[PDB]
Image: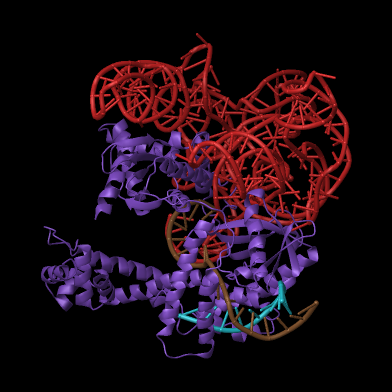
Chain colours: A purple, B red, C brown, D cyan
Amino acid sequence: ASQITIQARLISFESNRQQLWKLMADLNTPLINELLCQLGQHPDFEKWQQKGKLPSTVVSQLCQPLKTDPRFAGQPSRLYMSAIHIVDYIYKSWLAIQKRLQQQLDGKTRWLEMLNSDAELVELSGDTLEAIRVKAAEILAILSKTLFDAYQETEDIKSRSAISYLLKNGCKLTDKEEDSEKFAKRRRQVEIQIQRLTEKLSLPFPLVFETNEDMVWSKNQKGRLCVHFNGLSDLIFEVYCGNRQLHWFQRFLEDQQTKRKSKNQHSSGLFTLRNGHLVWLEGEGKGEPWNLHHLTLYCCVDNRLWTEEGTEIVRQEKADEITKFITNMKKKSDLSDTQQALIQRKQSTLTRINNSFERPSQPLYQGQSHILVGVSLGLEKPATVAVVDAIANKVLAYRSIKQLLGDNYELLNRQRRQQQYLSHERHKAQKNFSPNQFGASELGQHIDRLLAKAIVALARTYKAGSIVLPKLGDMREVVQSEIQAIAEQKFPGYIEGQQKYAKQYRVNVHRWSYGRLIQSIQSKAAQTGIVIEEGKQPIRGSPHDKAKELALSAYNLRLT
RNA sequence: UAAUAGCGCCGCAAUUCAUGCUGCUUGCAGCCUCUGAAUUUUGUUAAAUGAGGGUUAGUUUGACUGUAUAAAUACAGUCUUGCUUUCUGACCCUGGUAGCUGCUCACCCUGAUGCUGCUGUCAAUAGACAGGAUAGGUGCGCUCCCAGCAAUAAGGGCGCGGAUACUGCUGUAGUGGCUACUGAAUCACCCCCGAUCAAGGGGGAACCCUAAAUGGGUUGAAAGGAGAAGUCA
DNA sequence: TGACTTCTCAACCTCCTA
DNA sequence: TAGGAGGTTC
């Protein structure tokens, strides 16, 4: 899985864009709005929230009686299926948050009604917690996924209270056979949250085209690349890309022509194009929306398919997941009419997958993960690295933040200054204020990408097999402890001065964005081929020592 | 006149070290000369930082094929489109006229993450006019500090009216926001005519090659994953 | 507004036209 | 015969 997206503006006639704006802003988004509302008031909605799996076909079923509606008609099949898909996945994320809120409220009402304190536990249930806690401990600690699911399932007052007590007490050899505070705070926090939940119980949507061939490519008489989409072939758009992204688009036309010249003996499905959104960006100025906003294509390209050697890897992934799909469907005896069509399409792909298109030749680097580049995140130094051997105990080479961001350091300093300025402005914004993006930029993202590129390049230089990153959850405790450590480093025991310096430090050296950095490193390493493991950053020590010990802890846990 | 102190940065040291340097002794010995790391420690007649607002489908970071090359990388060949960004420059500016609106003010007192703070010129009024990013303080900034103002922090006091949730003492008066039209730059060696849902076309200069031929070249660089939704603050 | 979190990332088989 | 648009699916 190395999916990446390229983009290119689409230029066409005004009449060619008035059709696309009206078709989408007036008919396709309202279909998504109505499909979202209907999926919410569906009777089975609370059944879905209990699970994480909205049914495969439900969003489609609510759309078939909606395609013929007076206000949702005239949409191309791809436009309709895109809207359905939009409702499934846009409303997917929507109802995911929905069942978080709705089902959390339901559980809080329920836990409030059932879970109780130690005193009420003794009064109603009255079971000795040590005995049942130790029994459950010897049941689970002595595939524990089944046991954790069982804990997730047990809801009776005594059973849920005792199993949660065992889970939160350490579920292990703890000499303190105490702390009814576990389910006490459980019920208390539940009551507070149920109180809260009792009190509180201009751009159209994109066009996801899940089929690669729904975009048909052609070369203009001037040599420019052109696109027209399935369902709208009278609408022709010209690809205004950049030369860096051009070799993808020339690959699209070449790949499509190659399938044509073989009389569809080639499997679109090894295409370097997987799908493509068709969004409208936002323009500055005035005017009818089609003349202001720039239509933009967002093609998702599996970068692994570019090389011929990489294609065989994809050729092996699909030929394995699909031959399993066949066997999974071959055990059933239902033998539906259109089901056998689906069965038919599968063996068609297997036969069509062994016909190779011309792709470049690359000896994909083989990575031995024994080397462990360890990356340490903090406040004073935003990020430091340590290339350390694990079989030995020597550090091959450290690099600090001033040394990974070559010529990008002034960027870090001015980004810290900007993050100070923007935070002061947001605090000054109070509750009533104009939009707070005034003066904001994506300098933080540029730095979080420059840093990931350098870290991965350093890993590749030393043949590193893995890059180790701190768990993002432990990034508030770590920064708080680093502030404390700096405080006692400056003021030894003068507590007043320590607090004052902590305040003044938080004023200037703001918290970094340790989510975009971990995500950008995950993207870059995955693109290059370096697997990423996660360890536990040590609480104290010098940043270089913290990085080295993180890297070693990662290997120690890998040994398990 | 004053900016003390604090806090963050950035050098500059100084020391200790290796991820260095050096030596083979090949994992030890030195060394700090570069490169870093880690302290602390100054703010030099200075080193490096450096935050008023804007302007380019700017340039550079590119693809394929071949060669050298294990690779990188180099070189040659062929192609080239303008996306979204981060810088570095260069340049422009310190806006106007119209409307529509928001807030805040009887009067005190403290003083906020409050506002203001440039150079001349003419006043010395409170404002012009010229300049203009060097712009109160420190090497450089700050919510810190200094100076004025402070009704537009919050709190306290407290006069008269009307009401008996709260009002009035309030002038565009001061500061905001919005829209519409306008002012300048509209760029990447420079200049001119143009495109800007598309368009480039010309004309110079320096330099290099070349004696010399708009003969050719060259006249800043980098990075990519985008959409949607929800939650927290 | 910032920060976080979740999700998204087809494909050949038809029938139709030229 | 060679595309274009629709169809359907866990």
Residue A552 picture quarter: top left
Residue B173 lies left or right of residue A325; in this view the side is right
Rendering coords of residue A167 (x, y %): 22, 65
Residue A218 lies left or right of residue A446; in this view the side is right
Rendering coords of residue D4 (x, y %): 72, 74
Write the residue at 40% across / 85% down. A331
Rendering coords of residue A406 (x, y %): 49, 34
Tell me the quadrant of the picture where the C terminus of chain A can be found: bottom left
Instruction: In the rendered view, tell whether residue A105 sits above or below residue B120.
Output: below
Instruction: In the rendered view, tell whether residue A374 sits above or below residue A5.
Output: above
Rendering coords of residue A417 (x, y %): 51, 38
Q: Nearer the viewer, residue A243 or B190?
A: A243
Residue B191 picture quarter: top right
* Residue A200 visible: no
Q: Nearer the viewer, residue A167 or A114?
A: A167
Write the residue at 35% across / 44% down. A374
Residue A250 picture quarter: bottom right
Instruction: In the rendered view, tell whether residue A492 sits above or below residue B180.
Output: above
Write the residue at 44% across / 71% down. A321
Q: Nearer the viewer, residue A301 or B32?
A: A301
Q: Nearer the viewer, residue A356 or B82?
A: A356
Instruction: In the rendered view, tell whether residue A222 sits above or below residue A316.
Output: above
* Residue A204 visible: yes
Numbered disc total: 0
